[PDB]
Amino acid sequence: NTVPFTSAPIEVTIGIDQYSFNVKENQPFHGIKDIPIGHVHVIHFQHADNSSMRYGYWFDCRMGNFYIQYDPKDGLYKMMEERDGAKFENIVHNFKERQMMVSYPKIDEDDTWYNLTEFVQMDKIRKIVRKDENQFSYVDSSMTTVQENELSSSSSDPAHSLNYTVINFKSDKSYYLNTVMLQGIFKNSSNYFGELQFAFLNAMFFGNYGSSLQWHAMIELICSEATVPKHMLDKLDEILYYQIKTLPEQYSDILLNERVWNICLYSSFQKNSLHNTEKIMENKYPELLG
Image (cartoon, rainbow, N blue to C red; front, side):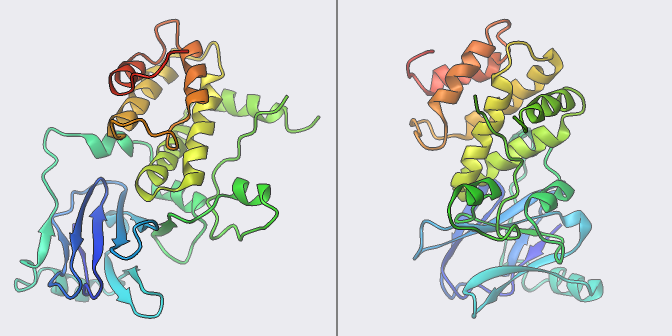
């Protein structure tokens, strides 16, 4: 499929999924062509002025035709759905502006993006990023989570808050909550893997700190188990492998937690349960062992 751009009036680093590039202010650009038919994609933006806040839009080309048009009032590149299909294809399939588009690289033998978004689906994202008026979902670098807001004395609306699954580790009520999740996860853990990956992606690309904590809280949820089903670990280890594989070679004190990782070493000591994960960890990060 194809996600066209109305214009590029402001210099901004325009990216799609893992890949990213930068457009110039007042530079001829009409969109991104030859987008691979996937299940979940994300297109982000990063202004040259502000190199801290990154905003993007999770979407799926299969459930509608989407384009990008700049808004002078908000000063942000907005995604909008084109309901009139006949008008959309006439804009896209026109010959003159298809040369102003950038072609999505043929993934070929590489399977990077799929291994990171294998369990991530839009109907799940819609339940995390609260919005129903649109088929896409706006996620910002500065966005807080529901758990993060209730922790703070201040408060934020659930719409602008990342409604991740709140996980607690203490020590009356709410103690039986964790054991019910673990049992539920042990069969048909799509929501878990999906949320794990999605929380990782927001933390990695957008730099969402709350998403970084959530990712660690979900890793800690399983790594705190001495005995967990093998079918779970074989997939988890693989999932955690490709995630660590995209992390920068230099030790990132903020993005990954040392305290949490040390308890995974204790958990995975029977196979080891996280064989492939530990392998790339010791090759990329020569830090002390647990």
